Structure formats: structure tokens, C-alpha cells
Image (cartoon, helix red, strand yellow):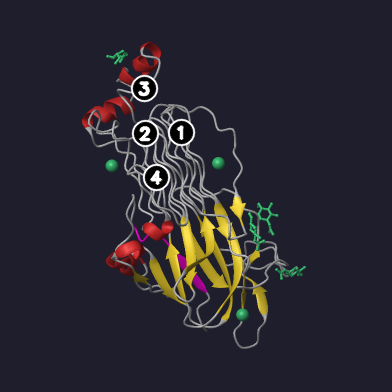
């Protein structure tokens, strides 16, 4: 029977740059999936996937998380989840960027930075106490998480379909969350610009002119993660770079997360100001499944499958027979479908 499940990952790649063709070939080897990875220009690191047949598809993409801070090691800002149902034609070309996680501050392979991570270096803390702010020993806030982009080409112009925002960069010192909401855009005339970049870099938007090195670049520019603070270097070896997919570079403050509209970062290197999560987007073409919650940690991914309405099942996981079109609630992970037709149970 034909294949209905397709899972796109970072192909084992991490950082501000995307995966290679060899990385994705090795990742999808022996799996029922093959893509062509871009190697030059703004498509470098983006996976091109050929639609096998004209049908209805569920495109659910998850953004990447930001990087941990240095002092508190408080848990990351997770990525945004977006799920959409689209009508696609055979041989259509989907362009899929899988956002990569922003660089964690700790641990570090640099010996002096590691002394700051384990806490046996009080230079940053005594600089905040005495000098009242960080301008000398800056850095330590993780870079912004790269966003996940799934877009199309129509008459020679990129058309976005699903953009899952990237998580904001956790600042160096952070014992607070404030649980910001996750924005989502549907009307396309709203400009998908970058996030505001201060000392730390802002997130990369959909299409903008990124002029700052530490800022994450937009999707149509390559979506490369930004560098760290110029002051974070030349004093430390501190590199907290934004993830691939518009992730903003890191400073003592957190870098902004990429998305349709880049996440805004701190403007004056605030050691406690995290980076804002990016702005997600879904095309007017297509139906929204579940509002844009933030769930997954680590790298992002994209799950595309032949759309089936499995809402009657207890868990929304069901498959359809290709010939007889008999839909059955999919269970098997060690379980067997119960007598009520839904709600899988453990058999043996
Ligand atoms: C604050 O004062 C001066 C300003 O540059 C600087 O030399 C000093 O090292 C700073 N304080 C600390 C604790 O670093
Ligand atoms: C667009 O998204 C916003 C934020 O999720 C929502 O409030 C608004 O109703 C949406 N508009 C349409 C037409 O779906
Ligand atoms: C999108 O928003 C702009 C203003 O924000 C408005 O002028 C335009 O008509 C909107 N597009 C649609 C399709 O509603
Ligand atoms: C899925 O099927 C249910 C009935 O089981 C229906 O109420 C719902 O509107 C359907 N959803 C979609 C997106 O077709
Ligand atoms: Ni958030
Ligand atoms: Ni590094
Ligand atoms: Zn179908």
C-alpha cells in the first residue's frame, strides 16, 4: 500500500547553518522519503520535496527552541506548533526549512567559559553588582531558536504555507517566564519583517533586509542564525548563535526567535530579558487544526501525512485502507484496538 507518512528533521544538523544533502540522505535512508537539499543561495539548507499525488495533506510543523542561559540554567523557551490542512497537486514542489535549536550557553568546550558555567567565575555577577550593568563581560544568553518554514513557488515567487515560530533565547540570568502568548498570522499583507535587534540579535522574518550580523536573517535571505555580540567576543569565547531558520544571535540578553515576523530581542543587553518567540503564520488557503500552542523542545520538525479525519478515535491517530477505504483507529505501539472501536488498550 502507498506511503502516507513523511517526517522531515534537521538531518542531524545543528547551529546557524542548515543540513547538507549527505546529511539528509543518511537521515532518510531506508525510509520512505527522499528530498533535494539546497546548497547555494538562499535555498542553502532548505529541503525540496516532491508531492507524490494530488490529494489533501496535513502539514504540521514545529519550530525550534531557544538556547539556555548561563547562570540559572532555566529550561528553554519551547517552539511553537502549527498544524494545517492543505490541498496540493501532484509534482508540486514544497520547500521545507526545519528550524534548528539556538545555541545553549552552557556547557562550553572553552575552558574559561566553562568556569563561568559551573559557577566558579564571579566576574559577571560582580560586574552587575559594582558596575551596575554588563558592558565589559557580556554574553551568556542563548541564541534564538530558528523557525520552521514550509512554502511553495507560484509563478516565480515564494508563497508561505506553514511557519512555526522559533523559541526565544533564554537570557543569562532568568528565574522568570511571564508566559508570553504565541502569535499567529493569517492575512498575508502584513509584512513579515525581522524582530527588533538591540545588543542581542532579533529573529529573522519572512522577507526583510538583514543588515546586522548578530540579527537572524529572513527566510528569503537564507535564514542563517546570527552571530553573538561583538562584545561577547574579543572578551570571552562566548558564542550563543541563533539557530538555522532566522534565529537571533545571543548576548547577555537572549536572542530573538525566528518566524514569519522575527522575535524582538532586548535593546540594551539586559541580563534578564529573554528573547521573544517569533510570529507564526498559516496561509489563508488551508484549514487550521489546533491553535498555535508551544510544546516541543530541542530541534524542530515537520510531519506531513495524507489528511484523514481521525477525530472519532480517542487519539487522533488513524489510517485508511487504500482499496476499501475502511478507516481504522491506528494503535500499534504494543497496544491493540479495544472493543469500542476507539481507545487502544494493551492486549497480551
Ligand atoms: C565598572 O567600572 C569600570 C568601568 O569600565 C570597569 O573598569 C570595572 O571593571 C567595572 N566593574 C567591574 C566589577 O567589572
Ligand atoms: C488570524 O489570527 C489571529 C490570531 O490567532 C486571530 O485572532 C484571527 O481571528 C485570525 N483571523 C482569521 C481570519 O482567521
Ligand atoms: C490584510 O490587512 C491589511 C491591513 O493590515 C488590509 O488592508 C488588507 O485588506 C488585509 N487583507 C485581507 C485579505 O483581508
Ligand atoms: C471531522 O469529522 C467530525 C465528525 O466525526 C466533524 O464534526 C468535523 O467537522 C470533521 N472535521 C473536519 C476538519 O472535516
Ligand atoms: Ni513564549
Ligand atoms: Ni559554539
Ligand atoms: Zn485523500
Label 4 and label 3: CA atoms lie apart by 22 Å
Give, as a single range, the part of the protein colored magenta: 5-12
Q: Examine the structure image and report whether residue 6 is included in the region drawn in magenta.
A: yes
Answer above or below: position of 125 versus 269: above
Q: Please name the residue that numbered disc 4 is placed on.
A: 102
Ligand 6 has an atom within 8 Å of the beta carbon of the residue at disc 2: no
State which image quarter holds ligand 5: top right
Q: Of the residues under marks 4 and 3, which one precedes in the sequence?
A: 4
Q: Nearer the viewer, mark 2 or mark 1?
A: 1
Q: Examine the structure image and report whether residue 212 is included in the region drawn in magenta.
A: no
Answer left or right for 247 relative to 277: left
Give residue 134's mark.
3
Label 2 and label 1: CA atoms lie apart by 9 Å
The answer to whether the residue labelled 3 contacts the one labelled 2, judged by CB atoms less than 8 Å apart, is no
Q: Please name the residue that numbered disc 2 is placed on.
A: 251
Q: Of the residues under marks 2 and 1, which one precedes in the sequence?
A: 2
The answer to whether the residue labelled 1 contacts the one labelled 4, judged by CB atoms less than 8 Å apart, is no
Label 1 and label 3: CA atoms lie apart by 13 Å
Ligand 1 has an atom within 8 Å of the beta carbon of the residue at disc 3: no
Closer-to-camera residue (338/20) = 20
Q: Residue at x 51, y 27 (%)?
A: 175
Label 2 and label 4: CA atoms lie apart by 12 Å
Give the secondary structure at mark 3: loop
Q: Residue at x 36, y 49 (%)?
A: 225
Closer-to-camera residue (3/168) = 168
* Most distant residue in the top direction: 130
Label 1 and label 4: CA atoms lie apart by 16 Å
Q: Of the residues under marks 1 and 3, which one precedes in the sequence?
A: 3
Q: Residue 195, how many percent across, how many down?
A: 47, 44
Q: Please name the residue that numbered disc 1 is placed on.
A: 266
Q: Residue 72, how many percent across, how many down?
A: 43, 27
Answer above or below: position of 127 versus 107: above
Amino acid at each position: 500500500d502507498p506511503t502516507v507518512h513523511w517526517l522531515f528533521t534537521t538531518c542531524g544538523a545543528s547551529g546557524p547553518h542548515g543540513p547538507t544533502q549527505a546529511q539528509c540522505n543518511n537521515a532518510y535512508q531506508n525510509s520512505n522519503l527522499s528530498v533535494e537539499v539546497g546548497s547555494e543561495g538562499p535555498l542553502k539548507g532548505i529541503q525540496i520535496w516532491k508531492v507524490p499525488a494530488t490529494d489533501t495533506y496535513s502539514i504540521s510543523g514545529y519550530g525550534a527552541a531557544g538556547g539556555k542561559g548561563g547562570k540559572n540554567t532555566m529550561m528553554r523557551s519551547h517552539g511553537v506548533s502549527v498544524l494545517g490542512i492543505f490541498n496540493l497537486e501532484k509534482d508540486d514542489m514544497l520547500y521545507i526549512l526545519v528550524g534548528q535549536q539556538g545555541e545553549d550557553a552552557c556547557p562550553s568546550t572553552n575552558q574559561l567559559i566553562q568556569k563561568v558555567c559551573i559557577g566558579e567565575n564571579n566576574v559577571i555577577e560582580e560586574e552587575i553588582r559594582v558596575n551596575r550593568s554588563v558592558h565589559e563581560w557580556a554574553g551568556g544568553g542563548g541564541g534564538g531558536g530558528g523557525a520552521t518554514y514550509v512554502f511553495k513557488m507560484k509563478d516565480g515567487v515564494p508563497v508561505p504555507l506553514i511557519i512555526a515560530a522559533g523559541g526565544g533565547g533564554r537570557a543569562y540570568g532568568a528565574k522568570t517566564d511571564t508566559f508570553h502568548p504565541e502569535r499567529l498570522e493569517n492575512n498575508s499583507s502584513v509584512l513579515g519583517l525581522n524582530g527588533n535587534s538591540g545588543a542581542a540579535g532579533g529573529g529573522g522574518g519572512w522577507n526583510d533586509n538583514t543588515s546586522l550580523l548578530w540579527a537572524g536573517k529572513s527566510l528569503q535571505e537564507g535564514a542563517t542564525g546570527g552571530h553573538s555580540c561583538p562584545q561577547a567576543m574579543k572578551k570571552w569565547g562566548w558564542e550563543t548563535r541563533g539557530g538555522f531558520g532566522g534565529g537571533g544571535g545571543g548576548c547577555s540578553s537572549g536572542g530573538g526567535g525566528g518566524g514569519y515576523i522575527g522575535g524582538n530581542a532586548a535593546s540594551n543587553n539586559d541580563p534578564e530579558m529573554d528573547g521573544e518567540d517569533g510570529v507564526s503564520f498559516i496561509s489563508p488557503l488551508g484549514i487550521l487544526y489546533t491553535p498555535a500552542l508551544k510544546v516541543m523542545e530541542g530541534h524542530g520538525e515537520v510531519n506531513i501525512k495524507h489528511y484523514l479525519n481521525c477525530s472519532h478515535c480517542e487519539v487522533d491517530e488513524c489510517h485508511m485502507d487504500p482499496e476499501s477505504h475502511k478507516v481504522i483507529c491506528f494503535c500499534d505501539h504494543g497496544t491493540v484496538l479495544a472493543e469500542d472501536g476507539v481507545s487502544c488498550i494493551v492486549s497480551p
